[PDB]
Image 1 (cartoon, rainbow, N blue to C red):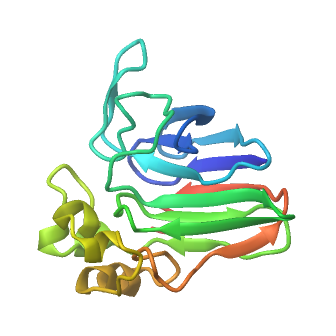
Image 2: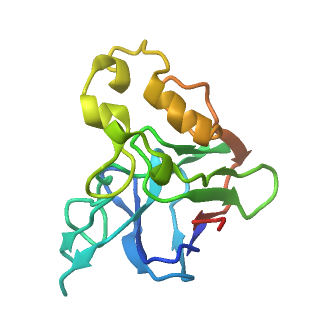
Length: 207
């Protein structure tokens, strides 16, 4: 499957793509404002994620640091990124269908649209100014709006036992972005697409 990753933000981002135990395609790349990077994701990929990283420094070997979404200091991510990270999430060719969502469960750094480029389903979007509006206690000094699990490490926010409810913090993310997951047991906002659809992930889709 192809995923065109487009940076419509006014700032550079370092896109990342991983399934947690491996890179997807090259795993990461710089995207200056306006650039597009098309990746190939193997059919059947389960639990894939795409995210943006901000304010990164890499050496000539591809090692460094980012302020949001850092994946073990690598340009070419093999592992998921450090919160806060707005997440484009997908599982492809799962009994004939693809499944996509956006999640704020690991916080929010950059606004995003995640849409099919092929027929048969809708896209989703979380493009509100979550960083600007972020509750004081969730603001990441390093940049972004942390989720409450990251900040407070409780069973209730992290849904550790499987039976957590919404919270004041989850409700903030949900109010700003109703179509994104706000906590682990949120009512799902997953879209079912035809199996083997192709997609575009756009950072900063709106002005």
